[PDB]
């Protein structure tokens, strides 16, 4: 039996994963639909990463005797072109990261160091997502948008 | 976009790494030159470890949007014989480790748990290095210097 | 070892030290920017100079000198790809100039084994210079954006 | 032995092979030098094709008890940028093809059907070179000079 | 950008390579045509050697920002029988080797050590060519002409 | 072939021939004492010099001179391992000095291929010198008995 | 402690091995230099065999507590053409064989049966050398000098 405020945080984090999963899945398919297959494939793997984050959160919530909340789906940020799509993912990650850090503070406070550890490993992974996303946005500026999309057409 | 003092702490640690890379590479080659090829190889391994520490710090700094400092090289503690060389390496590692604990404190205070994780990984490895060095100096007292060196002539 | 040979060899060593750190930082800068093929090529240049330094350090010790790894000259760090290449080029041209003077001096005291070491390093520095001048040249011919594009993925 | 006029024709064709060898090898090496390595390698291949054409003409001429002329080297057409280099190669090929068709007419007239066959193989291969070259000058127009060159940087 | 006088020397060494390629290639095929195929294969290999020296010289000239001269072809020294053919190659190598020594001296004088090194490699191979050729001429004296040729009929 | 270059090559060859016998005797002296690792290493030095000799012999003949395997100068034979190592070191320092002078002469008459050969030999002699000095330094640092002990078994 | 006179016999045999090693090495390289490579390969094998005999004599002498003499080198018999070379080698082997028989008597006389055995093996090998050398001299008479040298040009 875990602490109630930590379980609530785990659920908040899980809520954030549920959004990211659907948002990235849809963006991946949007990119695939437009023949930008490489963007589509990379986004798809981002989506699978969030699905695994979720899975670990769900196991942890149950082990601590909480109820995993898969019912509440927050606001998807869907873009209409590849540059908005990248910025929408990036805004979602920055929000996920704020929430991860407050959850980690809470775990530390009540000595739930195993939850803390799970949260730190997700955070490292969201920081990599941010890195990738900011880099793509930078590349579009350095190589020009048309060139960037050309380079992400074929796998 | 990370904290200014965290970046500065990472640059400090990076500075300690750069020192260790040069001191250890030089010690390693001095040992090879003397035909103490086992001590040379091991010291070469330590040098490569510190090169890999530097790499990871540089990448973290760049990602947090700081400027990695590879320009400032502190004082190399260069020994004149194997007992001095080991003790000089031990002195540098004890100093790197003190700096690493202070950097970790700050990362925790400002919620940069990914930087902290990197620093902890680096601290764990510096503590192995200290173990290696204290062990050697102890072996010199237990088996005698001439035996110690003889046992480290041939790889 | 002629004391002046050792001094030339420590001077080359000091150039190697600057190139190592300059190229390693430039490599990581390009990786950070997502230009991984430039990043990887530059990392490979950094490694070559680490190897030159190693051989310089072995030869100096053999001739009974003290390798200087304490003094680190000025890094030329660029802030965009063209400037980073030009910095790399400017460092190589300086390095190549010292190597030549060191080779003259080795010949004059008959340290022919030091001459051969340094001529091997020089050959590798001319290769580096060729790579650098070629990338500049290619930026002019294909355009900066296309050049960067073709160095994004490995 | 061979008809004297046929041997002269075979030598004129060899003469054209020797220009092309040298012109194509210099251009290959110019392209490599500029880091256009895909162009370089393809032009090197074209050079080698012509070395093999020379080799067969030399063998045939000696078999017909004629004297192969490798002393007279005509005018190399060297360009100073890639569009000029391709146009120079194409001008040379159109010249070579015209000489080939006239050597073949003459072989037919004097019943030297084996030399005709060798000449026809060479002609088929020059026709492939012409196609390669016209196609490249065409792609320059369709994809733009810069994009064309970009796509022939790396092998 | 290399030394004007160095580039002019490299072009003179190139001129010598271009003469040797054609001369040895013709000699090779004359020997093949006569059924002396071992002599023919060996001379072909010498030909290939020279082509490879040419390629090296061309790359270096282009790297020193010079203009390689494949336009001028000096005088082929062509023999009528195996003894004259070997002697003509030998005459040509000795001239080549004299030019090599002069160019090396010049590279040394202006500190182009990488060009000197290229030219020394070529020189070592030309001295191997001279050794080969002198040895054959000696063997023709020791074993008699007819025996020499008989031993070079089949590969 | 230039006559003074040929006489310089024959002089290098005379040094190689001394080195071969001295090193081979030293090797078998060490094997006979049961210091087999020293013996094996000395044997490998001996073979190196046999290969140096072979190479000089071919060059001398190509240049149309007469190789001299008739004159065999003074072997430096030690009586214990320190002294045997020091004799070899004194022979290498002599050899190296003659090498430098021959190389000077080859350069002055433009025999660059002979110079290349001599410079490869020299590089190898300087490696032999580094092995030798290094073993002598190791006797001082680990003790003569320890050093011998670590060179008993292969 | 070996018998002083056996050790002096052993050193005389070793003296002969050292002359043979140098004489055959040089004749081998003279054959290679002349392009007579099969003669040269075989002579080289002979020189190697004498190097092995010298090796075994050295070990024996040192085991018997004697001083091996590698300082004194007797007269090389060097020839100027292939017939002289072989006859020179033959004169050196007959001289070696006479000294070997005398050492074997001495060994037997003082009961050093292991030395006699080492020398017996050496003798059998010198007799094989003699067979090879007289056989080649015979062959020159039967097939002619020029045919003989022709058959020994290529390996
Ligand atoms: C005196 C300065 C240095 C010397 C002498 C030196 C020498 C070397 C050598 C010999 C190697 C292995 C080369 C090989 O693959 O054969 C190496 C590897 C490496 N170095 Fe350095 N180095 C120096 C400085 C640095 C610095 C400043 C960095 C900065 C991060 C660095 C990062 C690396 C990395 C990432 C590797 C590859 C390690 C691996 O094997 O995974 N080195 N260094
Ligand atoms: C008469 C003029 C020439 C003739 C007849 C000729 C003939 C040949 C032939 C038959 C080959 C082998 C082709 C194969 O792969 O089957 C060859 C290869 C080659 N040629 Fe030429 N060649 C000539 C001139 C040149 C010139 C002027 C160059 C200047 C660089 C050159 C450079 C080369 C090179 C680099 C190769 C590849 C050799 C190797 O790597 O094995 N050739 N040549
Ligand atoms: C005391 C005089 C010498 C002794 C005792 C000696 C002994 C030996 C031995 C034991 C070997 C290894 C043979 C085997 O079993 O394969 C060898 C190889 C060889 N020797 Fe000598 N040798 C002597 C002098 C010479 C001389 C004067 C030369 C002239 C160059 C020479 C040239 C060679 C060469 C080229 C090899 C083959 C090395 C290799 O590539 O492995 N040796 N010698
Ligand atoms: Fe996630
Ligand atoms: Fe909380
Ligand atoms: Fe994420
Ligand atoms: Fe990408
Ligand atoms: Fe497509
Ligand atoms: Fe470290
Ligand atoms: Fe702090
Ligand atoms: Fe450390
Ligand atoms: Fe370098
Ligand atoms: Fe100087
Ligand atoms: Fe460089
Ligand atoms: Fe053709
Ligand atoms: Fe006609
Ligand atoms: Fe063609
Ligand atoms: Fe193409
Ligand atoms: Fe590239
Ligand atoms: Fe050549
Ligand atoms: Fe000149
Ligand atoms: Fe040649
Ligand atoms: Fe036949
Ligand atoms: Fe030697
Ligand atoms: Fe001299
Ligand atoms: Fe040596
Ligand atoms: Fe050892
Ligand atoms: Fe034992
Ligand atoms: Fe023998
Ligand atoms: Fe007797
Ligand atoms: Fe024998
Ligand atoms: Fe035979
Ligand atoms: Fe042959
Ligand atoms: K493009």
Image (cartoon, coloured by chain):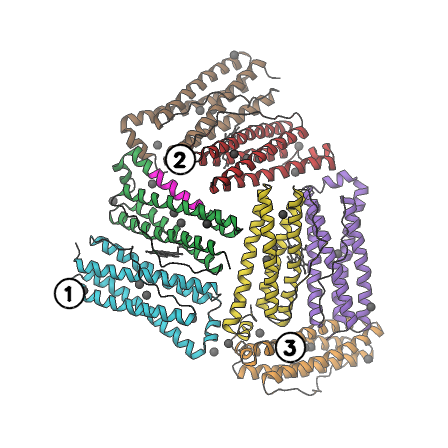
Chain colours: A orange, B purple, C yellow, D cyan, E green, F red, G brown
Q: Which mark is residue D109?
A: 1
Mark 1 vs 3: CB contact within 8 A: no
Does the numbered disc 2 mark a residue whose Cβ is under 8 Å from ligand 3?
Answer: no
Start and end of the magenta stretch? Answer: E123-136
Determine the residue located farthest toward the right in the rendered image: A110
Instruction: Please report the residue visible at 69 percent of the width from the left and 82 percent of the height from the top.
Output: A92
Residue G32, which numbered label? 2
Q: Position of residue B37 (x, y in %)?
A: 68, 44
E124 in the magenta segment: yes
Q: Is residue E28 left or right of residue B66?
A: left
Using the image, name the chain to which the residue with label 2 belongs. G
Q: Give the foreground label among 1 and 3.
A: 1
Helix, strand or loop status at disc 3: helix
* Ligand 6 is within 8 Å of the C-beta of the residue at disc 3: no
Rendering coords of residue F23 (x, y %): 58, 30
| Disc on res. E81 | none
User: Is there one chain holding both mark 1 and mark 3?
Assistant: no
Looking at the image, residue B128 sits to the left or right of residue D71; the answer is: right
In the picture provided, is G130 more to the left or to the right than G5?
Answer: left
| Quarter occupied by residue C38 | bottom right
Q: Are marks 3 and 2 in contact (CB under 8 Å)?
A: no
Residue G7 position within the rendered picture, expressed as x and y whole percent measured from the top left: 56, 17
Q: Residues within 10 Å of mark 3 (few under 14, many from 20)?
A: many
């Amino acid at each position: 039996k875990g602490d109630k405020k930590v379980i609530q945080h785990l659920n908040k984090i899980l809520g954030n994963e549920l959004i990211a999963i659907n948002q990235y899945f849809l963006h991946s398919r949007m990119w695939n639909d437009w023949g930008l297959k490489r963007l589509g494939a990379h986004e798809y793997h981002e989506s699978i990463d969030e699905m695994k984050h979720a899975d670990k959160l769900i196991e942890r919530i149950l082990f601590l005797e909480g109820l995993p909340n898969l019912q509440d789906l927050g606001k998807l940020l869907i873009g209409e072109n590849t540059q908005e799509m990248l910025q929408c993912d990036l805004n979602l990650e920055l929000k996920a990261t704020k929430d991860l850090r407050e959850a980690i503070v809470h775990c530390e406070q009540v000595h739930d160091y195993v939850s803390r550890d799970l949260l730190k490993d997700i955070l490292e992974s969201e920081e990599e997502h941010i890195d990738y996303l900011e880099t793509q946005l930078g590349l579009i500026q350095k190589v020009g948008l048309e060139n960037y999309l050309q380079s992400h057409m074929h796998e």
